[PDB]
Image (cartoon, rainbow, N blue to C red; front, side, top):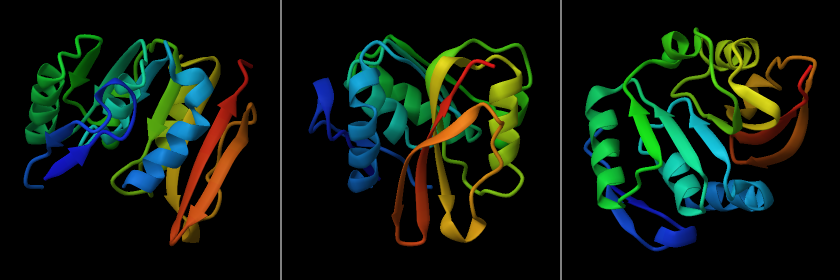
Length: 177
Ligand SMILES: [Cl-]
């Protein structure tokens, strides 16, 4: 497995992601371009780290990367060490346990769960209820079109949306209320 960082300080740098897309990341980070510098980012299901790593490359101030798979969390840590990225941490946890505590506010949150039903709406409510979001946070949500629009709290509004293939890529903006 290889991950390519397509932008920022490590643009073009290639990283191994063990035995277990560009246009997506391109679209998302174009949406995030004017807020990404010095942002605090949380990746709820970091997986390969594609999202968190691209965020750090583009001069995010910091990224907390949450990943349930121990082997995957370990490789992520190794890739951060390669890149000399000290302004990040990896927590080996499922998102439901992790977010069910008093949180810390983030400017940008990535919500791309490995499966939708049982995780997506639950994660969204925990983010909102436990203080994980800064006053005007952006939350990226990836979901199959077939699922419809996810239930979001009333103070979240749909900010950007792209549909490609079977998948809806969305960015919500949250108002502190
Ligand atoms: Cl989870």
